Image (cartoon, coloured by chain):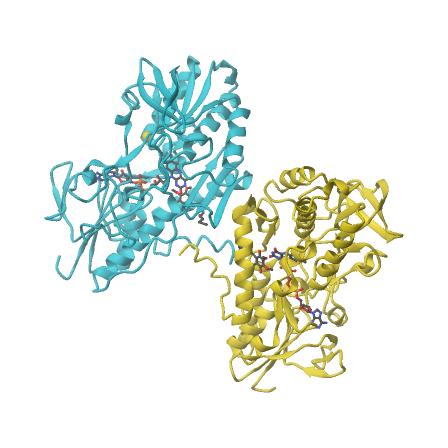
Chain colours: A yellow, B cyan
Amino acid sequence: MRGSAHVVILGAGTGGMPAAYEMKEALGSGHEVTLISANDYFQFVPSNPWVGVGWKERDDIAFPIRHYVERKGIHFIAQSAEQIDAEAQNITLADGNTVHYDYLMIATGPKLAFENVPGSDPHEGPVQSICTVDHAERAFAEYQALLREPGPIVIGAMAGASCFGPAYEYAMIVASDLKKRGMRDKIPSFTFITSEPYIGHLGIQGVGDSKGILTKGLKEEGIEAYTNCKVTKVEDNKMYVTQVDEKGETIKEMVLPVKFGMMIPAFKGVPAVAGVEGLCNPGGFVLVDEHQRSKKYANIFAAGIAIAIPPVETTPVPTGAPKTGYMIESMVSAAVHNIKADLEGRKGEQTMGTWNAVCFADMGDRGAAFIALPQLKPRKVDVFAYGRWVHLAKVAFEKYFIRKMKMGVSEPFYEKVLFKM
Amino acid sequence: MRGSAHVVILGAGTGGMPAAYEMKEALGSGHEVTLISANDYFQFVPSNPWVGVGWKERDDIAFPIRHYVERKGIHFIAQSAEQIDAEAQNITLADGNTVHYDYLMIATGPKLAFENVPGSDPHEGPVQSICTVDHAERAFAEYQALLREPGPIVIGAMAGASCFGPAYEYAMIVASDLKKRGMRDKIPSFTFITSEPYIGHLGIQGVGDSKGILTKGLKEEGIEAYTNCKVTKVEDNKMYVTQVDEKGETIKEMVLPVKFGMMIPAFKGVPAVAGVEGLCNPGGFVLVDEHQRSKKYANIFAAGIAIAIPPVETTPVPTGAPKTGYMIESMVSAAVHNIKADLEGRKGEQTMGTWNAVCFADMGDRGAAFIALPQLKPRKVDVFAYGRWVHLAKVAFEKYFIRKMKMGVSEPFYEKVLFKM
Ligand SMILES: Cc1cc2nc3c(=O)[nH]c(=O)nc-3n(C[C@H](O)[C@H](O)[C@H](O)COP(=O)(O)OP(=O)(O)OC[C@H]3O[C@@H](n4cnc5c(N)ncnc54)[C@H](O)[C@@H]3O)c2cc1C
Ligand SMILES: Cc1cc2nc3c(=O)[nH]c(=O)nc-3n(C[C@H](O)[C@H](O)[C@H](O)COP(=O)(O)OP(=O)(O)OC[C@H]3O[C@@H](n4cnc5c(N)ncnc54)[C@H](O)[C@@H]3O)c2cc1C
Ligand SMILES: CCCCCCCCCCC1=C(C)C(=O)C(OC)=C(OC)C1=O
Ligand SMILES: CCCCCCCCCCC1=C(C)C(=O)C(OC)=C(OC)C1=O
Ligand SMILES: [S]
Ligand SMILES: [S]
């Protein structure tokens, strides 16, 4: 309200949950901060691949949100937004209630566009997914069912995907698990299918020796890999694959039977956000400026996977670049600062900073991780590392982040640099 | 003097030059800051290997100090200290003059202990060195003489060495240069001799896949490599090598003829510092606490290669761990803060922080670099990277640091992190 702005954060994920705490800390008791999310629980998404192979469980990586944000003075609504009226500044919830805002920060993450590939929805066939804890459990359940009746395996990433690390990770840990149970030899064909133009492109034109290391890894595990692939449909428990050349021409079509499958889908913007006239690009991603502010609506900000970031290359089969945790947090931090500035008469000048991608993939005792920045080459940092110390860092970070999400974030978040100081 | 403390910095190198600027900035016009050094010029030491192969020249990497520090109010004495009387707080210079201090910060770097291996001094035989710009020129001169009368090459690192990166670097660029001139095939034997227990140990128990990458690199260039080696003497243009086993027992003795050679020597503390009773360990390195303060003299601080750091392993052939640039700068920053604190009644609490090693080795179009921390495994960061982007960073950093040494340093030096912000 006038003189007491009401700020709403839409989505309680990697970006949204920190956004709620930070917003409240920034604004204080004089302003209302409301967090709205489809689920009543936070999940640490980088852990989902492990849930999907049964190496972690839901209660290790998820917890109920209400108590933690409420004790900070944050209002929590465990309801999905179905409609956003940018003109009246009203959000319509699933239960038909409306919530008014003075400022809105959209942190809704990805819509999993299973509809791009008929039959690829985890509920429509054998092709599962590990992006959400709900789906990773379903993935594991199916994995258990492959244990009973072994058959062909197909793991990978669909056309349009932007999140490739997890595909490599899932394929490696499945291989690893097939052995620790002792049943790898029961598989007629383990196949990696990706829209990447080459192994380890990762949607970022490769990083360090990602190609050689990942290529060698898949071979070591007896996994046959195909690049430049798009799945046209999943039907009758068969995946129909078209492989193309550098110019898009078909070089082969394949019909792969699937007993157990997992393909990372393409991401789009969620429907409530995509549905706002003039807010988004055609993929449903919010068009924002360097300050995280909507180009159309001055009182709408956005952060996380939800924002649009222009491509910098165009691959034979459509692919996207990932939006990862450190950059997401920088976007959140910028949006919070600049909303505060708005409430006080100034144009916030804070930006998300240099584009970067960071990803940690834990294999069990050793992990691989990459750091790349900026987006285009030649980069200032282009590192792909492998070692047990990567595994140890992933373990350490998940523990940290989950704790921070329960205890609150002030904060110039990552002073996770004082492993130096 | 009383109420107006006189601070002396001994040595104008990677640690000492920044120390002078920072000290002066910290203290201001009310205190005298004197910088004393053996040479009247600063040299960027990581560039010396390239000087040693003729890929850089002295005037690209060195410049006269006087004007730059004097215009900051810093007094500069281009004289070597020969004696330090810790009790009277008097430094005796080469010309017999004495300089009194209230606080002394020792930044004298390494004494190159060529005397450990009879005949290994660059002026005594064919075994040269690239640690100083003076010696790297002499190295190149000899390289030019091998071009005229080709013969056996031996590059590597002596027992007791702590600086291995440069040995690998020099060996690779020499190979590279032998080809760009087209004369590699004229060499009867190119041999890498190291005190490391294995290739890529680097005095730090390896980092990432340093072993595999360096091993492969030496093979690619047609260089035969021997580990666990100590050179007993260089004589008659022959290097006498003893190779040992895990327990120190001789497993072979070798006599290698050398037309052109380069071995990184062991480092000790310089004589003026080692000569101070009770100041140093037996190697002549200053014993300091976490605050960079001498354990014996409260008004003596130290930074850089000059300080003692306890070993954490004991290798078949004696080796040391390197002291590198970022950690050196942290030591300098700590010493400055804590001297200032002393001048104002408090115990400075600032430390050098977590032990770390960083090293960049430029091969020409691509470079290798490593980052390791902390000292013992399992580490929080254990990365060894290779790529043209490493070369680009080395180029960028040398330009930066040289500029900073002419323009002055405030400073919380490395905010060379805003390639993020
Ligand atoms: C399998 C996987 C592994 C990954 N691993 C890493 C990694 O190791 N490192 C890294 O840096 N990044 C990783 N990422 C990427 C990125 O960090 C995560 O995707 C991160 O969770 C994205 O943050 P976000 O806040 O944009 O979206 P999310 O975390 O997905 O949160 C969006 C929130 O909005 C909610 N929401 C959606 N629609 C509505 C609606 N209409 N109304 C109300 N709420 C709604 C959702 O329920 C969700 O809570 C990984 C991603 C995936 C999929
Ligand atoms: C070949 C080589 C390559 C290296 N590459 C890297 C790298 O890539 N990255 C990295 O982080 N580190 C690197 N290092 C290591 C380290 O960063 C350098 O050795 C650095 O120069 C050490 O800093 P320092 O201040 O301790 O000593 P120095 O830079 O050696 O300075 C000591 C100064 O004290 C002076 N001095 C000595 N005795 C006296 C005396 N009695 N009186 C007056 N003055 C005296 C010397 O003339 C010198 O100016 C490299 C080292 C070497 C040898
Ligand atoms: C040099 C650029 C910054 C280095 C990155 C910081 C180290 C931690 C990894 C990043 C990360 C973030 C931020 C993160 O938010 C996240 O969760 C989604 C991860 O998955 C575990 C991450 O790996
Ligand atoms: C994560 C730990 C810190 C990262 C290091 C910063 C990046 C620059 C490299 C370090 C370096 C320093 C500090 C440095 O002082 C120096 O000169 C002696 C180098 O040689 C070129 C260096 O490579
Ligand atoms: S998913
Ligand atoms: S040297």
Q: Is residue B159 left or right of residue A8?
A: left
Corner quadrant of residue A108: bottom right
The image quarter containing residue B342 is: bottom left
Image: A245 above or below B214: below
Say above or below: A355 vs A23. Answer: above
Quarter that holds the N terminus of chain B = bottom left
- The relative height of residue A243 versus residue A404 in the rendered view (above or below) is above
In the orientation shown, which residue stands out farthest toward the right? A236
A4 left or right, relative to A222: left
Q: Quadrant of ligand 1?
A: bottom right
> How many badges with numbers are in the image?
0
Residue B408 can be seen in this image: no
Asked if residue A337 lies left or right of residue A177, the reply is: left
Residue B249 in view: yes
Instruction: Name the one closer to the observer, A245 or B234.
Output: B234
Q: Residue furthest bottom?
A: A2
Q: State whether residue A21 is above or below residue A122.
A: below
Percent x, y for residue A164? 68, 51
Residue plotted at (80% across, 54% down): A127
Q: Is residue B312 rendered to the left or right of residue A49?
A: left
Observer-nearest residue: A218 or B120?
A218
Q: Residue at x 86, y 42 (%)?
A: A253
* Residue A182 image point, x, y percent: 69, 44
- x, y percent for residue B414: 41, 53
Horizontal and vertical percent for residue A255?
86, 44
